[PDB]
Amino acid sequence: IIGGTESKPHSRPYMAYLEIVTSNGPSKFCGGFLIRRNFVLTAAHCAGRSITVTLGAHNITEEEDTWQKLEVIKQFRHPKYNTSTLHHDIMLLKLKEKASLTLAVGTLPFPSQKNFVPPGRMCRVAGWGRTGVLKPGSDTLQEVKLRLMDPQACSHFRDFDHNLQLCVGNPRKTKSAFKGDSGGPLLCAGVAQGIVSYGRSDAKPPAVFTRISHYRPWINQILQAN
Ligand SMILES: Cc1cccc2cccc(Cn3c(C(=O)O)cc4ccccc43)c12
Ligand SMILES: [Zn+2]
Image (cartoon, rainbow, N blue to C red; front, side, top):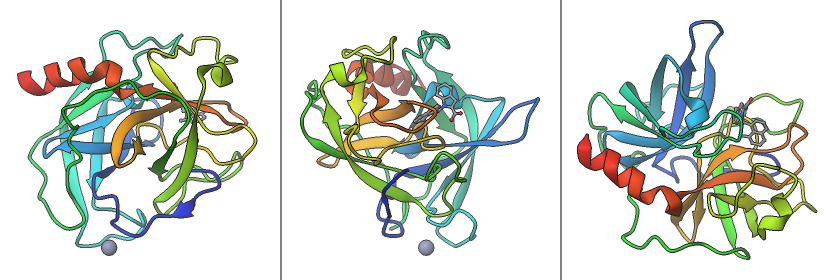
């Protein structure tokens, strides 16, 4: 998160910190969010050979009783995820066991309604990602308030599509999701409407988020079958 504030500790109890293993490089990291006691939503580009989820974290360098470190038993990457266009950048992770509900850990289920969210309003995103181009991932959970933009603001992303994705962050400010915030929720009036996907390497906003409303049928189909 660039240009944000430190979250109040444990104030976003659905937030998940993902450690991503690959066979041919060191660990990588993403965010995500708990939508059922045994399911985390994140970005498809966060897939790996194996993943471990930490729930209940604030400072990810300091072990505490709120932590739950949980094994992922299976990854459900969207079957149409495209590494060229980056369309359909969404994935569900099934946890080996259901998480414990505490003050610091809880779900964020979708409401019944799945209305298309138009441009104009302010929403908020949280993550442990980099705080600038030359800066390392934050030890503490950070968050920032960003403007939903008209889709023409994201035209320069030549594979951007308004039906599939949200355009997020006023270009006149530095405030943005960035590298390492991958997979985190964009909440608009307390409802998850987006998932951090991608942006510019130089961190100039806006960035591109997956539009959750488009994928609600797919999300439901995985949950009901598993
Ligand atoms: C999340 C994010 C936000 C803003 C700007 C970004 C600029 C570049 C990449 C990312 C995230 N990202 C990464 C990575 O290296 O972090 C690899 C990758 C592959 C497919 C899709 C997204 C991807 C950005
Ligand atoms: Zn604590």
